[PDB]
Amino acid sequence: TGRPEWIWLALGTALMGLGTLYFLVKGMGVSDPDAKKFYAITTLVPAIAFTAYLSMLLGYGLTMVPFGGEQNPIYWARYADWLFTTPLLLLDLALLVDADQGTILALVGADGIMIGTGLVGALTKVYSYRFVWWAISTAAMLYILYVLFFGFTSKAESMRPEVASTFKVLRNVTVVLWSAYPVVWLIGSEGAGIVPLNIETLLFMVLDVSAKVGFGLILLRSRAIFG
Ligand SMILES: *C/C=C(C)/C=C/C=C(C)/C=C/C1=C(C)CCCC1(C)C
Image (cartoon, rainbow, N blue to C red; front, side, top):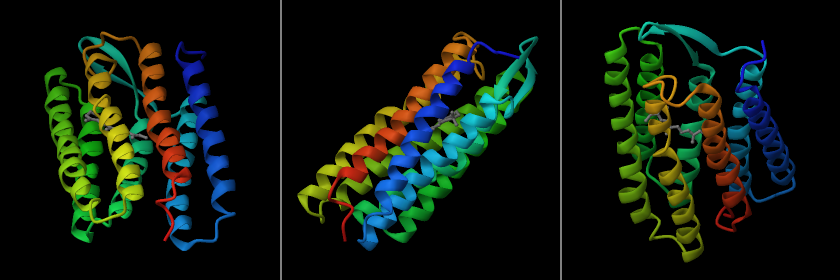
């Protein structure tokens, strides 16, 4: 085959792999129970992403969806990746500020709708409806972001400054990155088809890598993970 975006897939594969191993190695040398918790979660995130990037690199997770009079290439392997990586990231943040069980369930469920409608939208054949699904998926995301910003930040105030200040950073990196995904989708292959697939793939690998390995390095080097 040799599609124009493969080099971005090979690069996402690579970065996700090194990040997985470094976290794995750093996580099995720590004795603290809580630290082990955050470590097991944060290493699983880039591990799921590495397998998904590898599959796509090798020709899987791709389907030709018909709409707009064209045969559009939609990488569905992404949603298979984000379906488990996104709620796991949310969990790290909820465990950090001592989010309540009810809070966590609702964030994971919201996350579920977001990825579900997102994929359903990316597979829809009626061009206009693709945007009806995209619309719902984004509304779910804003719910998640509102909670992280208005709820979590508030509960992180009963924590120590070291924990509150680490969460702020992760909360900020998450808000900036997640907000970018609905936009790439809209002007890319699953949407308006303005940005070509090769560029779109590069945009996604930068967000995925920053939101997983970036987020991970920040959380795992902090002392807020210790019980
Ligand atoms: C490691 C991956 C991360 C942090 C992925 C975050 C992904 C999102 C915030 C995705 C959002 C989407 C929408 C708001 C609507 C359209 C489809 C999605 C799934 C691309």
